[PDB]
Image 1 (cartoon, rainbow, N blue to C red):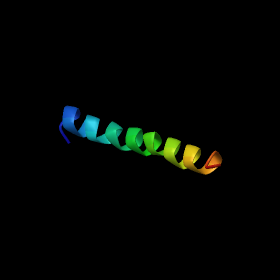
Image 2 (image 1 turned 30 degrees about the vertical axis):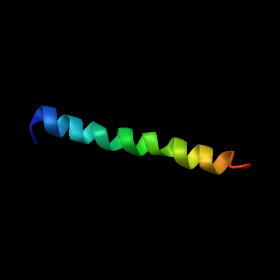
Image 3 (image 1 turned 90 degrees about the horizontal axis):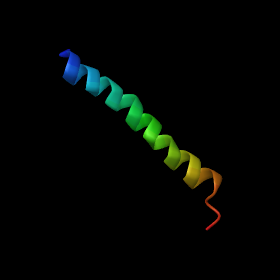
Image 4 (image 1 turned 90 degrees about the vertical axis):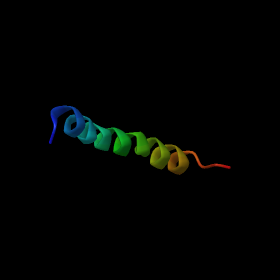
Length: 33
């Protein structure tokens, strides 16, 4: 709940989740290897 921790732990979630899509996008859309 502390604005810094909680605030960062909250953004850390979507940033990771969204930093994950590139792996679900690349390794799925261009896995021609």
